[PDB]
Length: 428
Length: 18
Ligand SMILES: O=C(O)CCC(=O)C(=O)O
Ligand SMILES: [Fe+3]
Image: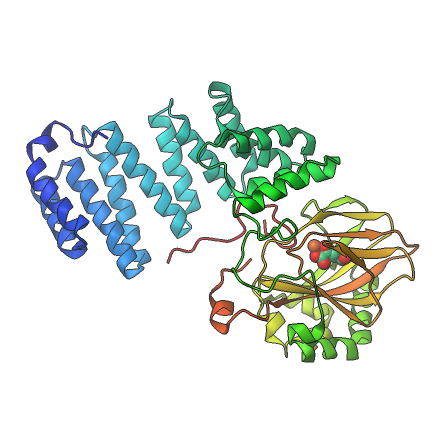
């Protein structure tokens, strides 16, 4: 990579000396070394880039967002200098975007990537990076347009193929997404061996009835993406006891389970009252997990945060639950009423994390037509009784009764998680 | 969007620096 313009080649000796200090771990001394080069040579792009890299390393040594914010600006200063070589310009702004994403400045990272695409219009990899930027902010429409441009000039780019197929599947274009996901994974290009693409390829195949779906769950498991063929969560803590169905004693949460079963009728009655007098609080399921039917949820807690307006509708239930931080503090779970009507079939799916267990309390259960499968075992609900399963295992639900079915869903931390882990895991 | 019951989003967590 050509990093020295005409002037920097003349001071290459001073530049290499400072870089050796940064490479020797003496970051604080290399910071002042490159700062002195920037003072003496204010137009040197290599001296400016060296100052940015040292600020980057110092931000890690101290885990400082404020220091990294300065490095982000210094990387941009490199681009504003005259006669900057193309390799140095690309490297500074790409790293700036990467650090903007690390800080959560996703809007800023997008502008940096847009500037790179304008500067190097032929580099398709920068377009692929711009596509990821749109995906990180949820703009699947602009991401789709980007990967369509990449596939027009580079039709066999595997990175662009899997990301196009992911967007297609997200838009419920199930049958269309499969060739892009399969051929993209099979390309072996960097960035295509990702669990997210094995997950959605196998799920797309399941929804169209293709038997090849479980062959891809096998390969995903063999490559280290899934704990097993059945358990396909992607945000995991390794080593947690993996088991489809649990008993209350196994979870250790006996006091919560007894409290739910002893007081189940009051939980039912507050849910029925919301159905009758405030049905707008029940929101339709919005993750494209239904094949058909009507399925809605009324959420009291999410990501360990109490929903204040929701607890005004179920005040006694919220008061009862606030005694159990193992569920109210579960930042990777929810507490919610869940209603399902006849004619509903929920696609096989898994949750995102192995760090929770999911409890179901039966509230209004018709005598026939309702069942839930987890892994290879199908069960039914009982009014006033708790079922416990690990929803990181593939599960599927049917509702073919003659009236509605109402349950209460209570997520808890996996019992084997230490208190330190429950406080540090990013919320989902 | 949030990953409440499945893995529908490209990423399910948020970045907040260090
Ligand atoms: O039966 C329900 O209401 C929800 C089933 C389900 O997929 C879950 O509990 O995660
Ligand atoms: Fe589920």
